[PDB]
Image: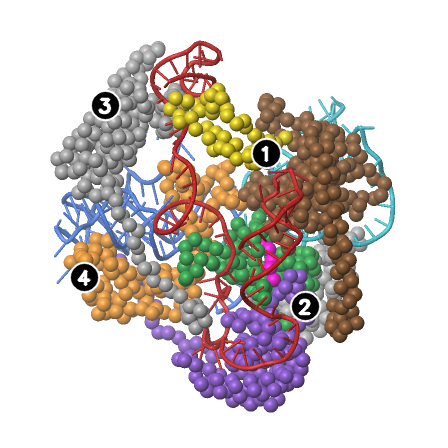
Chain colours: A yellow, D green, E orange, F brown, G purple, H cyan, I blue, J red
RNA sequence: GGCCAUUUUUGGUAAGCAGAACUGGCGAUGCGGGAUGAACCGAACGUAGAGUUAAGGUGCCGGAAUACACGCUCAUCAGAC
RNA sequence: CUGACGAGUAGGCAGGCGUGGAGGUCAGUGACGAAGCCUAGACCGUAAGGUCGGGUCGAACGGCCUCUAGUGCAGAUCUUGG
RNA sequence: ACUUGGCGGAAAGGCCUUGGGUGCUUGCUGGCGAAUUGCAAUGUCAUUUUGCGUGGGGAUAAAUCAUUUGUAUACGACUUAG
């Protein structure tokens, strides 16, 4: 098997945004900004 | 050894190509007729065909005419020996022994 | 007054030696490699942190059976160590070369430690006492340090020679056969 | 015209060898399109050039050539013993090479 | 120029180093015949070093000749060099390793006017 | 003479393909052997099963990891049968085995290119009719290759995606055949027939 | 003395060469070179070109002309060994080829006498060439090996 | 201080055992082949170039015909000198 | 000038390379720098080895014809020093 | 080189198709030039990456050490927190 695509949610909580940083306190917490801006349209990329 | 019965052609080609002489030993090439003349005019022989004639027509002075020639130094055969193994008899499929007239073929690949 | 192989300008450099120092040679070599090539202010602010166990000296050549450590992750090496006596005898020479550069009229912002080497000194023999009445040596391995600091400078631009060419007649007969066609 | 090739392309092979020796003086060439020794009797004497690129540009170019010639045939499948002026560097085993059409027999 | 001499063939140009000249520092690189019972250089196997032997001797027409074609000859003073006035394009001078620089300019100024080739004119030049 | 020689592995013999492929790599040809799971071995199925189960017992005593590696894929059975030919412990052998690519099925850079066969390696041009043979998919499956059906599924896709193409070619050549009928009886076709073409 | 002077000094007297027995003798070309044969040049600036053969010179070379109005290959020496000789012929009679010699070429713009002799030869050559079909186009082409061309099988 | 091998051979059940006889070697001997092996096959070596071969081989490693020809053999322990 | 021939341990003989010192000679070299040392710089000799250039250095040393020997090193669980 | 849509995930990164624009046409007949590179010596016509200059688009963070944790630990490592 081979993962070809993965689709994330719209607004992830602060429990999985804390999973993607080793140092949560210094970080600018900028995970999934340019991905959650893909719901700004009608979702044509995400429906794709 | 491989021996046989040479014809006139192979004797002629050997004495013209690989035939050398023994002059106080001194293996000397038989280029001129003056060598054979000055070394065997005691014995009648005075040209190179006189040596070939004392070879093939085995004559009274064959011993000295043969012993004047240095032994021939042949190549390896230019077509192979014809067999996979030399050291069986020519009757069993090798090379050694009596092969009578076919010796001519082998000598014309070694000359 | 002879030093190692230096490819630096002796006008803009300052030197400090400190011979026959009873230190550890295998630890002074590693702190001399750890200091090497850095700017002198970064060097003196690094060696004041080695003494506080804040940053470690990377043991690279003389490093077998050393305990691996975490601070060596700064330099990619598991095995590192904090040689306090060696770093004291190195930073003494650093302030000595800083003073010898201030006495020569050099600007202390462009200094980088350029040439620093250590090499073995005559060993100081003492003696152990071992089982069944033997005696084996117990020797110091003191060091000869030396270092040379230099003001760094820029604009070493890459102008070079002309490289005169040996092209043949039948090559220029094609090169000039294109100005009649295109160029 | 898209083709300018006046050479038959061939492949360098191993040196002249036994199982356990090798003679670097006489190289083996596998000419394309040749299958018999009677066919490989044509390419005798024809000049072979190996062509390779280099780092230091000398004489106005980066491409350096080693020359040589075909000497004799080899095997019953059209291999060709060829010598060179300086022998091929034993790293080109599987490299293309150019059997030119001169000295012309025809 | 020189004498008309044939193409200078130098059968083995590589130097016959000793066996194990590299592996040990005590074993110098000067040649010694291997003499062991088990030895493989005396017994001349394949892939082992080649020994000096009389087959590698040079041609007597081109022996002792430099690649310019002249036999070299050590010259201490001016009187030794004037033993080569007759033979200019057969021998070539070569100035020794203990001649001072006040005499090398004299020897070179003489060998220029006598046409004798010096194989080291650049020794101890006062540039 | 091509830059890459793509070989359809179907209906060939493992050793007799491996010999010619190993010799063509050592001369400077790039060879990709596609569809290696339909490759053949002489002898019945159980002869080759007990020749692989006598290879599968040969690991290192003290550490089973570092021993011989018993690859199960048919492309890797063929690759083991190939790299025993090429002297792979040199550098010439490594630059030989880097010219080779052996796959299972036909991956989709290589399904659009023409696939050749090696006639001195086919099972039909070598074996006497009556001798049993062994398709390498069966042999690899009974020693633990997990993916046979999956490859079959993809093959059961691609032939369809090829066969339509074949119609999309073949009818086209039908039209070309009519063109090769309408150029006849002219002067130029007779002059081409005079010069052989 | 820092080196003992030797006893015998080999004399500087050069010897003459021995009287050699090697006479000069005119070249006999191969059986496929006849004046008028269309040649294919194989090397030099004009490789691959097709050219018309003329008078055999006396320095073991061949004199060829294109004609220059067709392909661009002027009156030029080309060695006989770097040339594939095809089978086609043109009639060579009617051209005053015998003016040319080895003295006519010498390394020391283009001399106008060469242009004049070029045009004088090429007018008669093109007047001969126009009699056969397609040969004017054939000389203006180049030769090149296509794929699957085996030159031990190709009959020129 | 010897050893090995062919033919003859004594003792011994037998030996890569002990002891004799003819010759050849190895010891002192490289080299090409027997995948490796002091003595088996070939052939005994100054330094190089060219050609032809010996013993062995020509699917691939490995240079050389997956040559030609007539048959035999299928081995859930092939056989390859 | 011509011809033949060229494995070799133990061993025998010959021609030679090197070292300390002695008689002779080159009216030899030399503090405008001898000997020594270093030198992936060079030349010669089959080889022992000889020679030159560069750096270092600080006062003596070589070529040849002969004489003489406490004369040549990878190994001796070799000696001393490191 | 634009454009139009469809198909292709096994390693799709390619294939097919629409409408124009520009260029060439050896499909056929022509005119000029192509010499001197001087009798062969690749007659230099593939690329890939690093780096540096210019122009035009886009975005503006992490990790480690030190402190801490004990579901982890000889040391590192691991899991945590600020």
Residue G60 visible in rendering: no
Q: Where is residue D76 in the image (x, y as percent from the top left)?
A: 69, 57
Mark 2 chain: G
User: How many C-alpha atoms fall within 10 Å of the one at disc 2: few (<14), some, or many (≥20)?
Assistant: few
- Disc 4 to disc 3: CB gap under 8 Å: no
Q: Mark 3 points at which residue?
A: C88
Q: Which of J29 and E20 is in front in this view?
A: J29
User: CA gap, disc 1 to disc 2?
Assistant: 64 Å
Residue F67 shown left or right of residue J55 in the figure: right
The quarter of the picture where the C terminus of chain F appears is bottom right
Q: Mark 4 points at which residue?
A: E105
Mark 1 chain: A
Q: Position of residue B67 (x, y in %)?
A: 65, 65
**Which contiguous range is marked in magenta?**
D6-12
Tag of residue A47 = 1
| Name of the residue lying farthest toward the front | A42
Question: How many callouts does the rendering have?
Answer: 4
User: CA gap, disc 2 to disc 3?
Assistant: 87 Å
Residue in view at x 52 percent, y 86 percent: G119
Residue in view at x 39 percent, y 22 percent: A25
User: CA gap, disc 4 to disc 1?
Assistant: 95 Å
Tag of residue G154 = 2
Q: Nearer the viewer, residue F128 or E124?
A: F128
């Amino acid at each position: 098997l081979r993962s070809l695509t993965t689709v994330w949610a719209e607004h992830l909580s602060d429990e999985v945004k804390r999973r993607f940083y080793k140092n949560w306190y210094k970080s600018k917490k900028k995970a999934f900004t340019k991905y959650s801006a893909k719901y700004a349209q009608d979702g044509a990329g995400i429906e794709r | 050894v491989a021996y046989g019965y040479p014809s006139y052609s192979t004797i002629r080609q050997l004495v013209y190509k690989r035939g050398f002489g023994k002059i106080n030993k001194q293996r000397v090439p038989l280029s001129d007729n003056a060598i054979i003349e000055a070394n065997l005019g005691k014995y009648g022989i005075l040209s190179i065909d006189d040596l070939i004639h004392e070879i093939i027509t085995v004559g009274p002075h064959f011993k000295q005419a043969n012993n004047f020639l240095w032994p021939f130094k042949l190549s390896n055969p230019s077509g192979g020996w014809g067999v996979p193994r030399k050291f069986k008899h020519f009757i069993q499929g090798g090379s050694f022994g009596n092969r009578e007239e076919f010796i001519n073929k082998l000598v014309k690949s070694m000359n | 007054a002879r030093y190692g192989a230096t490819s630096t300008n002796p006008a803009k450099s300052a030197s400090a030696r400190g011979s026959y120092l009873r230190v550890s040679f295998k630890n002074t070599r590693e702190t001399a490699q750890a200091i090497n090539g850095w700017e002198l202010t970064k060097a003196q602010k690094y060696l004041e942190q080695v003494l506080d166990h804040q940053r470690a000296i990377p043991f690279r050549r003389f490093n077998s059976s050393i305990g691996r450590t975490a601070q060596g992750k700064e330099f990619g090496v598991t095995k590192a160590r904090w040689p306090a006596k060696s770093v004291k005898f190195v930073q003494g020479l650093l302030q000595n070369a800083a003073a010898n550069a201030e006495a020569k009229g050099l600007d202390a912002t462009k200094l980088y430690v350029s040439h620093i080497q250590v090499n073995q000194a005559p060993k100081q023999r003492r003696r152990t006492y071992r089982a069944h009445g033997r005696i084996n040596k117990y020797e110091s391995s003191p060091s000869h340090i030396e270092l040379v600091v230099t003001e760094k400078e820029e604009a070493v631009a890459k102008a070079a020679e002309k490289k005169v060419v040996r092209l043949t007649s039948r090559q220029r007969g094609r090169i000039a056969a294109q100005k009649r066609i295109a160029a | 015209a898209e083709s300018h090739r006046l050479y038959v392309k061939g492949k360098h092979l191993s040196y002249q060898r036994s199982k356990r020796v090798n003679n670097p003086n006489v190289s083996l060439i596998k000419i394309e399109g040749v299958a018999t020794p009677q066919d490989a009797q044509f390419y005798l004497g024809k000049r072979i050039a190996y062509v390779y690129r280099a780092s230091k540009e000398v004489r106005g170019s980066k491409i350096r050539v080693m020359w040589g010639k075909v000497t004799r045939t080899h095997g019953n499948s059209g291999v060709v013993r060829a010598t060179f002026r300086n022998n091929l560097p034993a790293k080109t085993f599987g490299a293309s090479v150019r059997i030119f059409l001169y000295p012309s027999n025809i | 120029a020189s004498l008309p001499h044939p193409k200078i063939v130098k059968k083995h140009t590589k130097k016959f180093k000793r066996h194990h000249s590299d592996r040990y520092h005590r074993v110098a690189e000067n040649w010694r015949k291997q003499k062991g019972i088990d030895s493989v250089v005396r017994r001349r196997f394949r892939g082992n070093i080649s020994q000096p032997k009389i087959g590698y001797g040079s041609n007597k027409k081109t022996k002792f000749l430099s690649p310019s074609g002249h036999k070299t000859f050590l010259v201490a003073n001016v009187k030794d060099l004037e033993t080569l006035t007759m033979h200019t394009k057969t021998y070539a001078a070569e100035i020794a390793h203990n001649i001072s620089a006040k005499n090398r300019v004299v020897i070179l100024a003489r060998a220029k006017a006598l046409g004798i080739k010096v194989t080291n004119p650049k020794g101890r030049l006062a540039l | 003479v091509e830059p890459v020689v793509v070989i359809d592995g179907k209906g060939h013999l493992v050793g007799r393909l491996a010999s010619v492929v190993a010799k063509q790599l050592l001369n400077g040809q790039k060879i990709v052997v596609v569809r290696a799971e339909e490759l053949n071995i002489s002898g019945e199925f159980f002869r080759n099963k007990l020749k692989y189960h006598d290879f599968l017992r040969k690991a290192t005593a003290f550490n089973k990891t570092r021993g011989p590696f018993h690859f199960r894929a048919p492309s890797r059975i063929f690759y083991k049968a190939l790299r025993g030919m090429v002297s792979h412990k040199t550098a010439r052998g490594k630059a030989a085995l880097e010219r080779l690519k052996v796959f299972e099925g036909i991956p989709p850079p290589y399904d659009k290119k023409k696939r050749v066969v090696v006639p001195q390696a086919l099972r039909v041009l070598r074996l006497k009719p009556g001798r049993k043979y062994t398709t390498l998919g069966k042999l690899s499956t009974s020693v633990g290759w997990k993916y046979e059906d999956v490859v079959a599924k993809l093959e059961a896709k691609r032939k369809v995606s090829s066969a339509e193409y074949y119609a999309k070619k073949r009818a086209f050549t039908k039209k070309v055949a009519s063109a090769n009928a309408t150029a006849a009886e002219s002067d130029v076709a007779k002059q081409l027939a005079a010069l052989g073409y | 003395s820092a080196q003992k002077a030797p006893k015998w000094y080999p004399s500087e007297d050069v010897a003459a060469l021995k009287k050699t027995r090697k006479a000069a003798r005119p070249q006999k070309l191969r059986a496929s070179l006849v004046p008028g044969t269309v040649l294919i040049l194989l090397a030099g600036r004009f490789r691959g070109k097709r050219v018309v053969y003329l008078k055999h010179l006396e320095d073991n070379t061949l004199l060829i002309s294109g004609p220059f109005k067709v392909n661009g290959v002027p009156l030029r020496r080309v060695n006989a060994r770097y040339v594939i000789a095809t089978s086609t012929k043109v009639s060579v009679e009617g051209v005053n080829v015998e003016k040319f010699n080895v003295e006519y070429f010498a390394k020391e713009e283009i001399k106008a006498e060469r242009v004049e002799d070029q045009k004088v030869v090429d007018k008669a050559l093109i007047a001969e060439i126009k009699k056969t079909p397609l040969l004017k186009q054939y000389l203006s082409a180049s030769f090149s090996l296509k794929n699957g061309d085996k030159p031990h099988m190709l009959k020129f």
